[PDB]
Image (tube, rainbow, N blue to C red; front, side, top):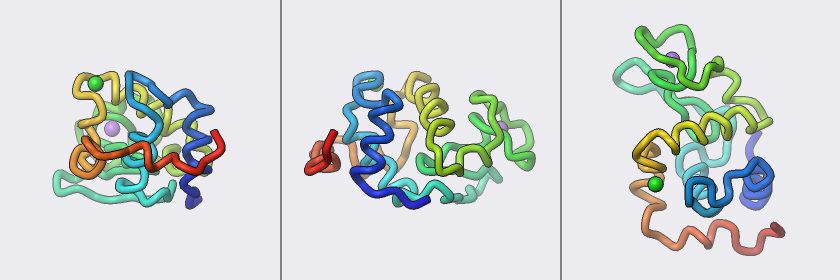
Length: 129
Ligand SMILES: [Cl-]
Ligand code: NA
């Protein structure tokens, strides 16, 4: 599923991401935009053999199991395919674990390079929340 901007913001808010670990809702929408272009089915393979899955491009080396990343940890205890569903519940629950891990949202390269320090509030403007 390809989410709309305000559609995703509302879905993320209902799942408790607004101000989760101090990150306002706009940070999460901005990260999803530049990680996956709001597409839950996005996948991207990395040079180390791992693959990033879903709307927040969660990596298979640490967080989910795709059966082809030797020595991965699967810290979210979920198949990576679950992160591609139109229901973003699995991706949000796993992202909550990632953002609490230590470096906050810097774990998302696209957020660090394209959202951090910008006017992220613009990503929820006009939305009925
Ligand atoms: Cl933080
Ligand atoms: Na894994």
